[PDB]
Amino acid sequence: ARIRHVQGDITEFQGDAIVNAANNYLKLGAGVAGAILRKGGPSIQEECDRIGKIRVGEAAVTGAGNLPVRYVIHAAVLGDEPASLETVRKATKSALEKAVELGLKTVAFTSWGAWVGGLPAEAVHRVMFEEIKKAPDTLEVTGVHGTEKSAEAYRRALLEH
């Protein structure tokens, strides 16, 4: 799938879905998840509770409440097991699979930086980008970054070569 990198708040993404990095228990806390629970509203955690625990490396879909997407795809990168490059690979793949199953066209991810601090940053990026590349061209993926400097740096890396 094609990727485009922009600066923004992922909770303001106007497309079909956002991916929320998650624990496998599917319980929301602070950060992106906190913005989701506040701006999305109570229905998101309520539906996560309905789904129940999933395995690390899996994903699960909820509605998005008052957010301007249709779905939140929760990607379980850690929880009852630690994050690894394999859990990152699996969770990314699983999230993309849910998007494809739902027949979606536009899906946003963050860098997942706040979930992978003990892993090598460049390898995390490589694993995620490889999974996104393998996804069908029926998907357009947006990488949402906190700053313009970072968004542009990610675009720059796609020239290289």
Image (spheres, rainbow, N blue to C red):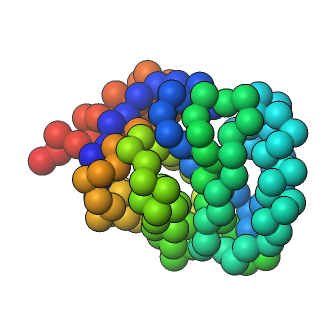
Tell me: 41 left or right of 95: right
Outermost residue on the left side: it is 161
Q: In which quarter of the image is residue 127?
A: bottom left
Q: Is residue 148 left or right of residue 110?
A: left
Q: Is residue 84 visible?
A: no
62 or 7: nearer the eye? Answer: 62
Foreground: 32 or 60?
A: 60
Horizontal and vertical percent position of residue 108: 48, 41
Number of numbered callouts drawn? 0
Query: In the drawing, does residue 66 fall left or right of residue 10?
Result: right
The x, y position of residue 73, in whole percent, is 60, 53
Picture residue at 49% right of the left edge, 56% below the top: 102
The residue depicted at 46 percent of the width and 44 percent of the height is 107
Q: Where is residue 19 in the image (x, y as percent from the top left)?
A: 57, 49
Q: Which of 134 and 47 is in front in this view?
A: 47
| Residue 87 is at least partly visible in this image | yes
Identified at 30% across, 51% down, the residue is: 138
